[PDB]
Length: 125
Length: 125
Ligand SMILES: C[C@]12CCc3c(ccc4cc(O)ccc34)[C@@H]1CCC2=O
Ligand SMILES: C[C@]12CCc3c(ccc4cc(O)ccc34)[C@@H]1CCC2=O
Image (cartoon, rainbow over all chains, first blue to last red; front, side, top):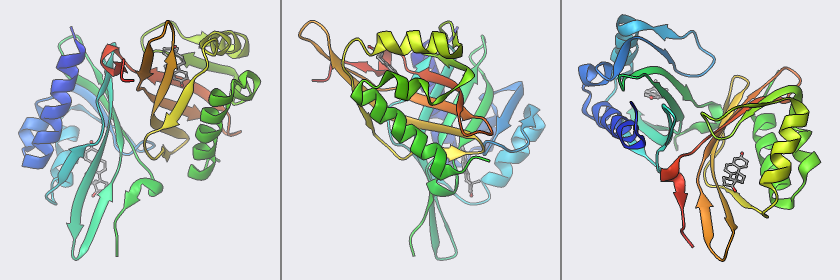
């Protein structure tokens, strides 16, 4: 069972774990055979081990992530808009993706797809 | 192939046709075999006929559609956040979905899914 509020709670927990750099808190939100496709059009990482290495490498740089709009949640699915900022040696970068989570009966995320492209990667001078 | 610029333009075309009541301008965006699942979870309308029939009814009440954020486009896929305002019995309603379009090689829309739930429906006048 996945009510709109549980799915929203998971998204917030997710954003908070990213900010915290809590690698195990992120992975604990995924099902054992869950898939991650980040960004869309890339070979999908399947399972806990692959999911974990993916985030371990992403967390190499401290992230600052923010939800920019209400979470859309319906029928075991949720989609949200957010921003991920991080500096890279004087270079501040802001990525603006839209993620899509698919949940399972247990309330764990079974699929994650992060949709962003060159046009969503911003970052200054 | 599908460039970000194209996919983004299709979305902007879509929102315009929708604002104008331009049914055929919308049906033209899809492929002969395209599918629509609006909302996510409901039975998906397949093919131009079913898609036409679906949009013909949705348009019964003149819509005021607006893009609330930048389009996310990458690898034959695009997702965008927006609002659909209208009235029905003196009451104003604002639906805030996040759409997901998948394009074919020809640049046409083969799949569309609308993700919004009770939480994204506001009487916000
Ligand atoms: C990988 C990344 C850091 C994390 C991250 C990115 C893009 C989309 C994401 C979506 C997520 O749900 C979680 C993390 C990211 C950035 C792409 C460029 C970069 O440095
Ligand atoms: C169906 C609808 C009119 C059209 C519409 C809605 C919601 C999401 C949409 C997403 C689209 O991409 C195109 C049209 C709609 C409204 C839900 C309530 C309503 O009257």
